[PDB]
Length: 540
Image (cartoon, rainbow, N blue to C red; front, side, top):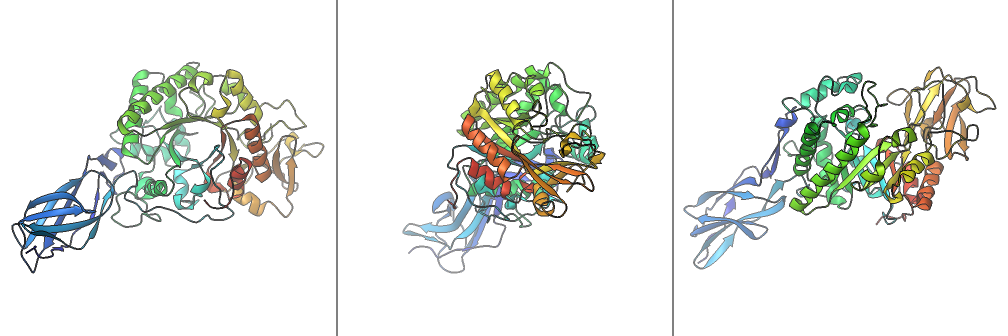
């Protein structure tokens, strides 16, 4: 007759195709990619015949077989695909097979295929929206935001976005390569730690702990292979397959290395590391280049050259080729985008009309036009048009867009940016006609986390009452609050301004909208971004 029903023995049931050392500090010791996971299963049989053949079934599909030589046994086999499988041990003989009860084994992989959907409820003022406008709706999630700001991936209103850019991927490099970091507490030191033993100009992860080791909703088990933001983003892709999650390389303090990319030897090394990166972390849909201004004028005052414009176009070209190479190997489609300055002076230092042919989207940083970094010339930090008191204002959203359109850039590539934060000055004075922007400041305004910057959340919750004056400049399409006694002036985006930009995007037939760090919003900004772009409400 058929064999007796076997029983699965005690033993770890979680494995991974891509192993991650939950204790490593160096990127080169953090991950090791394997073509398949090494699984092992043992069983017992206290009653009945042991059969002649033993098989390991994964979801009913045979994954291993071998002679059944005793009432007990062990099977070692490979699993080349991630997922949660119902594993069974079956004993078989001439007349019949007998399977044991199912035991779940997890075979982890960086695409999150082993994780249950991370479908969290919208928080704060966030309201549901369907991405049915065909327009881009993106936002940035900062890696470091999981600390003080305590804003994790599970707090992201993922259903109200089409693109999600990661809080910046660094480029390895010490003195002379990433000096701009030295200005931030232990940041430079952190990067050297991650890049220990790694060639300079290669991609890396800035905060390994926050990225893959910190426990977070959905990935809290002490023995889960991928935790932190990455782990969560993997689960997030399971819930929102169509969501494009893109790693942004660069940023204000990590753009320094780009200025060396003129040397193709380094550029090739960079493009190669990015590819290996995309192969390693499958949840990512491409790459975002945030070279904080080619030509200088960035965080580092000693970098920038006329050669930068050409380098940028070359970089995008080579990256696009690399992604194409990758598509041929995975069959997937990858997006290539970039965040650029909205100022015409910087936009002209690059031939975007040519680079656009390799890029999917161009995220126009139409914000930070003004700020505490200049106490003499004040203005709207993210306005749409020039104000009435200075119609010849240079830094405005429209000018930025026009500059691009002028070069020959297709409007569909342009994604206008909105701010979920405000910039402000303190002790403003010497203004006339009651327009604070015409005076000068004595210093930066007290910020939420750092001087001169305040989350929209704090603006809407603390500076929308009391002695604060609220004003919406209809000419420029931008709001601002002012406290006469202390001279505190704050410029930011609000539902109305964002709505103005949305209709503007709809009119000029631009790509869409995106915002700087989703952690600073309470929902008003993103809600408006969606509504103004045509997305229908109600959960889908």
